[PDB]
Amino acid sequence: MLGFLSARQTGLEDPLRLRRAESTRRVLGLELNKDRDVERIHGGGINTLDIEPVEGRYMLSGGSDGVIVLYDLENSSRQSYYTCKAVCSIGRDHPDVHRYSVETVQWYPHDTGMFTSSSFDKTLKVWDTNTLQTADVFNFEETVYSHHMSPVSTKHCLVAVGTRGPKVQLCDLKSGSCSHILQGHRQEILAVSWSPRYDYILATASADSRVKLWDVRRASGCLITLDQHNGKKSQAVESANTAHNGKVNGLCFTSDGLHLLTVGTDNRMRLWNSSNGENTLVNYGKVCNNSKKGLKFTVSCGCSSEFVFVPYGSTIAVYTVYSGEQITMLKGHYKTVDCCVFQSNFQELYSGSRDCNILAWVPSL
Amino acid sequence: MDQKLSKLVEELTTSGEPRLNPEKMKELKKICKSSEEQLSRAYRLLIAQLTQEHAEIRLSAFQIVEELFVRSHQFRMLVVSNFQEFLELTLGTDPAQPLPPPREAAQRLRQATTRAVEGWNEKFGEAYKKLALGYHFLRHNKKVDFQD
Amino acid sequence: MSYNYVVTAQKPTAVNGCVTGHFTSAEDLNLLIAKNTRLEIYVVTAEGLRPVKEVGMYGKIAVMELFRPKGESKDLLFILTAKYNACILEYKQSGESIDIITRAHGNVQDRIGRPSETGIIGIIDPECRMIGLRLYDGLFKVIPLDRDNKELKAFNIRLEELHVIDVKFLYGCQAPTICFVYQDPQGRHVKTYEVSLREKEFNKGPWKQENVEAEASMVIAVPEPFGGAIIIGQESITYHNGDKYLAIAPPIIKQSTIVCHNRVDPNGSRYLLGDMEGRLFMLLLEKEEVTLKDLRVELLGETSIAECLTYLDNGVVFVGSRLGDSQLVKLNVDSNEQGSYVVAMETFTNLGPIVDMCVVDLERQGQGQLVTCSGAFKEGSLRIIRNGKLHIRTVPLYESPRKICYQEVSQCFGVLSSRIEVQGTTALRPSASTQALSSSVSSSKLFSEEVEVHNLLIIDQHTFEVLHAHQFLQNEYALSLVSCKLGKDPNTYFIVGTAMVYPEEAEPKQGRIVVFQYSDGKLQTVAEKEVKGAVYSMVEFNGKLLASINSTVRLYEWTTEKELRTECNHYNNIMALYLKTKGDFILVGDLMRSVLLLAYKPMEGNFEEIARDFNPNWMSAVEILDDDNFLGAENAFNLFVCQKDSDEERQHLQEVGLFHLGEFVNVFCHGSLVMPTQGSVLFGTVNGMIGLVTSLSESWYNLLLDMQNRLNKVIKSVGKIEHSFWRSFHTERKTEPATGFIDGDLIESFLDISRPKMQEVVANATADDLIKVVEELTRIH
Amino acid sequence: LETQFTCPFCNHEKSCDVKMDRARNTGVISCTVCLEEFQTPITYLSEPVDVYSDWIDACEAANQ
Ligand SMILES: [Zn+2]
């Protein structure tokens, strides 16, 4: 590493080299945090986490008990040991608390003054973070499994919602229009994710073992349907062209948005060319998941090699996205891990699981 | 020097005694203090015993584990490395993996491991936050009655 | 909010790109040299180079290539900036007036994307149908040229290979054909595509992928008579044309990797190749009646460590260097009796990577003097800089200098240096450490291909001769150096922080702080202290030694027994790389937490974290301007000033100033090169620029700001790049406008405009008042 | 009396399965969807409705 510092000082290597190499080294040295703790307030398992995209300071967490906790991740104390204190809380005494489990919570991109939370109580609530009051509510005829706002859209502000209905809802936060729907799936839509690269590209994964990419501006259904075999087993499109041999319960675009990682209940993760949905045949081995709802997993950013952190039983499996090589198992949870969210500023990880714990993984040394 | 250690551990555990016979336990203490890899060899012996199907044998193995825990620090790091499996094998938390017979020895194992875990939370909890996680998980998620 | 004035004392001198062609006139042979922000246009005369223009781009020139579209009388220049400002420029001379008109311009920054490891690549189709940019992994941006744009509209073609090493356009292909080397887990392969502008997509290349050398790192597009390409790797040179597969493995190129090339002949019968060790080779293509017969490589000789090189004519080669002085060398037909055909005609000074620098009032005048550790392995040297224009001496060390400190009592400089030995070990050249008057080696009881040997050079501060050269332990890297007297004894010591570097580990676990005293022309080891990590930085702190072992900033006291005793530690750092001091306060520059205002409370005897900045800036240098202003340099070429704000929120340092310098600042230092503004902080950069930061007053800063906006409205940039965008604080995960910083170069450009333009600037006091103000601003450097 | 119950946590109908371990006098109710689990003592007169009852009661008590 002194070689890295010397090369940076002497201009031999771009500082990009040291930055991404050290980010990768930090991610590889991920371990149970020696001096850090997260305050425990959820009475039930944490189903979702979200660190705000700008300044990466505050973290939302939705629990199976319906409460939403807002934590400050910064060590505002002077000690090396600190607990991520809870700033705010939609608790059981809040007038607008979710009646059932909160399954997805997401900070509004471009601004930390608002966030959103969808629950199995058939509601997508939009909260003002300052007053901590519901600015809006969208009701659905069937329970919400996931939702996502575009991390890129300066123009549109649509929330793509996947419920147990076979339709992907698009709720306009600009003047409230939840009527827009996308047809083409056949069972519950367990995951939805906007492309970080393209403004109007949305990937939706449903229990019909299919993943569809939509240009929501378009009037002609999905753009691409992901196919495991790319055409080896080709059939007229009524039941073929499946992404997995089970329910596809998780989506994640890579950092650049040029590839898509789909995890399904066939104990398989697959990497897809996001421009034509071709399977890249990256192996990843066996990725154990049996979740009946959406599975939240994230990818690394700002590193020499991209990593993907997938909940794997009661562990976090870290894989290399483009080679599939298994990095490691982060092993500190006592029950199945529901979500993991990656802090890209310091290569940190926060994992929420059914054991009512949010565990922080920090690079060692 | 592994033969005598496997032996001594075997007579300690297979005997099924209510209480640890003192002088051979002292021999175990000395010869476990001798080397660190051989202390961890004793740890593997304990782990292999703890999976085996008899409540008295699991009780003997757990009491040896408690002796080394209160007596050794690298043992504390090594056991907190897999405290999850340690709790699965001691407390019988998972319904799919309950404790073998007899019922009396299993009950004594439950009481002894609850109280030992209480003592470990009081004495080494701050140095091992994973022990704190395990204690908290037992006290709320599994609702283990520590007052029993 | 803070008020800062940044001005370039010395313009950047390191050449990061050089291209030749007919830019100024159809008959002129121009040499365009890209120093970091400066584009220098020379005309290649029969002797030397005649400078015809020097323009200052609002951008770091990452790409610079000349191309002649069909029907164009003379070459157009394509420049891409590090912030992805693309511009096509034309040279228009109207008598005395010279103008670089922006024929086209645009910004090609993708909103998201992983910037490629091997860096920005820019190529132009040999028939000038398009510009191909590799800016991000997995993408290949294309700017069509047949569609004559004035906005440089571009489109991305998805490239299935995500780790592309190098790419070129092939010659003699009916369609734009790219040949590129890429890395996949199976190895490195060279593949070809044919780009289609109509279908906006790749098509199957003329010849299929071929598995190339593991370190195949360079692609050279051979001209039409041969066609195909040449791939240069670490160990072999191969030539592919689709069915011709020539290969050589010259043993003479094995010792160092080839990093640059240039085509000597228009038909590519000869190429120049520079290595990192400075060796210059000629690669010859032997033709047979045309196809290619056989490849030969012959060592022409040795030059400066060449970032780039360009054959001008008549055996003259411009060797543009980033690590040393640029050269204009002659390729003789016959050897010089030492096996070398290269002869240096001219040397252009280059303050290389300014890793460290000290301001000294040598000769006991009132004038400062910068002594800078410039350059690198073979081009390492000391540069002494004064105001006389700036006069620059050079003291070649022939080894990389790393740190420098002045010991006034001993009348010498302590310079940390590093040389490469190949084998026990053998020096590759006679370096300044080996040419000392006297020498010594450390015999320490604490610890018991090519390697770096680190030395402490005691250099006489009159003659700049190496009075002494103390070699350190085997596999020991000296990182920090400070000249100070500790405790209460009167002796002044050279205190050196070191680290034990072995290949088996990523972070040093061992190191020591060695206290030397230089007296009677000898360097006696006064004291040692085994520490448990690399001592990245040390500073004298109120008579004590404040050191930074890997993540711990700790304080040592100098006892009556002349030994170092720990007094206090602070551990809340990732790695404390940079340490500064003013009073009881310490400023800890961290690798990625970016600052920490620490305070040593003497009434108790420990540190206290007064404040911190929680933004994740990766640091290169740090300094303390005032009691409550803290300057810091981020590795993304930005300056930022943090301020102690005015509860726990008081522990948050507020970034009150932001600025994009465009340079990698390596060192700050209080001082000035001269005999209205408060303070003076000189800084040294990687591309050789020396700059100067001063604090301004509020009203004056506001007035200056106003002038900056007016000049931006008046002065026209070369690439039509907005100055605010150029100076906007930029990082891969952040982008903000410049605040709290005045661009001194832009203000000082107020002199170089005609009076009507001044009146345009000063539409809403008189112009003469502002001329006086800018003159006074120029006085400080 | 139905044996499959709506989960109080995820509101998924008939997603809760009840296991009566009579040998240990314990009833375990688990939701298949959200994987929430609850354990209560049971008697020989107990039924899955009683286990789901104890679960609802424990939820309401813990949520006070
Ligand atoms: Zn449920």
Image: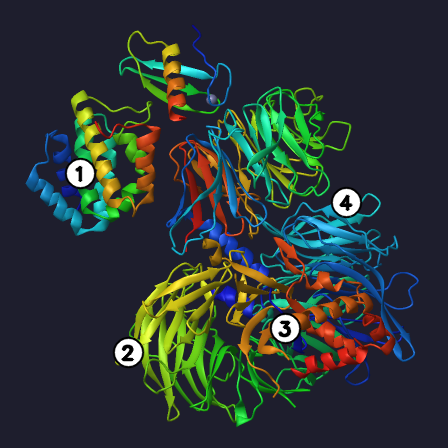
Look at the picture and state if C358 lies above or below C266.
below
Q: In this view, does C542 lie to the left or right of C358?
A: left
Q: What element carries label 1?
A: helix
- Gap in Å between the C-alphas at discs 2 and 1? 50 Å
Q: Earlier in the sequence, mark 3 or mark 2?
A: 2
Mark 2–mark 1 CB contact (< 8 Å): no
Subunit of label 1: B
Q: Which of marks 4 and 2 is in front?
A: 2
- Gap in Å between the C-alphas at discs 4 and 1? 71 Å
Q: Can residue C52 be seen in this view?
A: no
Q: Nearer the viewer, mark 2 or mark 1?
A: 2
- Gap in Å between the C-alphas at discs 3 and 2? 44 Å
Instruction: Report which residue position mark 2 lands on.
Output: C559
Q: Position of residue C767 (x, y in %)?
A: 80, 77
Q: Are marks 3 and 1 on the same chain?
A: no
The three-letter amino acid code for the residue at tag 2 is Thr
Q: Which of marks 4 and 3 is nearer the N terminus?
A: 4
Subunit of label 2: C
The three-letter amino acid code for the residue at tag 4 is Asn
Q: What element carries label 4?
A: strand
Look at the picture and state if C180 lies above or below C638.
above
Disc 1 under 8 Å from ligand 1? The reply is: no
Instruction: Report which residue position mark 1 lands on.
Output: B64
Quadrant in which the C terminus of chain C is drawn: bottom right
The three-letter amino acid code for the residue at tag 1 is Ile
Other residues around mark 2 within 10 Å, as few (<14) / some (14–19) / many (≥20)? some
- Gap in Å between the C-alphas at discs 4 and 2? 75 Å
Instruction: Report which residue position mark 4 lands on.
Output: C203
